[PDB]
Length: 78
Image (cartoon, rainbow, N blue to C red; front, side, top):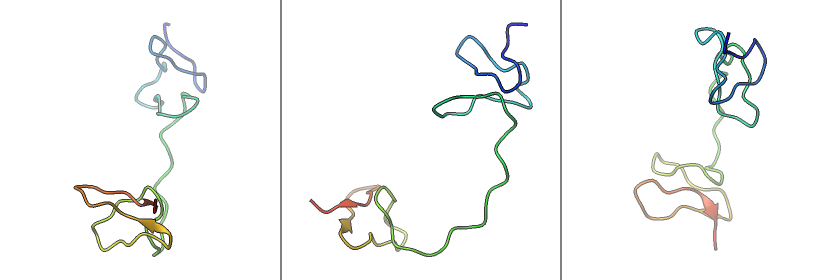
């Protein structure tokens, strides 16, 4: 009682009947499904795309650049 069935949508007042199994993930439409699948193999080498963080030897792709601050982010050179 007072809970969203399995797969059903969950809200602030309506929490998944099974929290240990299902949860309310942050996304467009929060569902009551099991935790996400295992993490996929590490990504391949590539330049830092827009939004990516710089500092760990990561250079923004052609046309993009990173600002000078604590935690900058690649962005189209203005």
